[PDB]
Amino acid sequence: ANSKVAFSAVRSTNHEMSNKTRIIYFDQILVNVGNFFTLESVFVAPRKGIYSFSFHVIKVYQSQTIQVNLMLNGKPVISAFAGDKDVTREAATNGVLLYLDKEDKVYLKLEKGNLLGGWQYSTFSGFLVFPL
Amino acid sequence: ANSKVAFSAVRSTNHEPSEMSNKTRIIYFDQILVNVGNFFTLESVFVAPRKGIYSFSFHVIKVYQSQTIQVNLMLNGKPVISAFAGDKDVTREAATNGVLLYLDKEDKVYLKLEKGNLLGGWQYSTFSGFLVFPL
Amino acid sequence: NSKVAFSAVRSTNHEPSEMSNKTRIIYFDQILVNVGNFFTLESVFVAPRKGIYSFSFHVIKVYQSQTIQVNLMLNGKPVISAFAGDKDVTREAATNGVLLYLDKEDKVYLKLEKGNLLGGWQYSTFSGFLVFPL
Ligand SMILES: *[C@@H]1O[C@H](CO)[C@@H](O)[C@H](O)[C@H]1NC(C)=O
Picture 1 (spheres, rainbow over the protein chains, first blue to last red):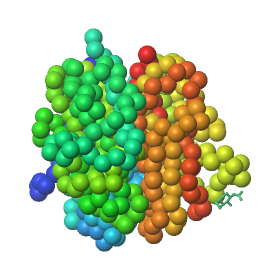
Picture 2 (cartoon, each protein chain N blue to C red):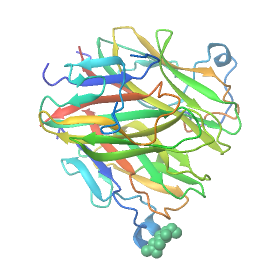
Picture 3 (cartoon, protein in one colour):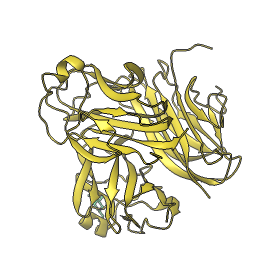
């Protein structure tokens, strides 16, 4: 039970972010065991452990560049990029394992760019690999 | 019981799609690296043995030039996530994505070539997945 | 060792070592996770026990003029490949991922099969974990 933690979220075409935080949100929740993925955007770790994270953020409008940072408690840990102005729906993708303690916050930030065209079909997933 | 489940497959040649695959549009992988539980069948379809959360990932590599491709991860005949590879005039291009799904027993997960033809083959393409935890 | 995982990042834009140029092994300086310490300082993973392991990588470059091919290697042999390059963009990633059956002491690592890492490979990642022992 308490060792079972996972979330998976997708950006659809729903039409329900700030220049400060620039948090990328995912409206369609596919998995949320434990309900620790909150506000369509932020994962809050329930316990100390190793967690897997992966994401694909779609650069839809072709002539733009984006940079996406995976954030841990307000600080960047990994980065992804998409800036091929010949390509439509190019993914800025990366993944990582992290050592998290209880109440650690992990989310995606649009560090650079504007996601012109929207970011439909973008994905963001995470799960507890094992507790420590 | 059936708590260890995982598969992993790769397209090892540049051979063209089979005549059957042109009518189902289901992308298949001939080289099976992992198939614990033997739940990955027909070199293409994963059948969930039990209720739980399952991870999936895929990298479909197209050559130049098959037309712009769209790959959907399918769950019981309906698309869940999609990836795109529009040509950037290079020798090879990749349509990639991954996701966690809540699956029930006998649920079927597979890859569909929604758009495009994969002319020139899809060598080096990969498709993987595993049970994260039963539910 | 039921709990085995590593995750590593290339944190700088520094050129590869002369040794690295010789071995073609892509190395990572920043280790975020290394439970069991089976990911060595030479950026090679040594499987502690028989089991199914997950591996993912992203090799990111700022200079993409020439083609790069990255192979995931298992005891000196390629298992999967990733391609990038021959482009002029901000940053591009050669990426792929796979599950592998490993026997104990099997060696898994990234080799630059084609191309170079002129300009550095900052922000590149390489991760792996034991899904379950067999
Ligand atoms: C290794 O090769 C790269 C690519 O040509 C080059 O930039 C780098 O300077 C080489 N390393 C050394 C120590 O010369």
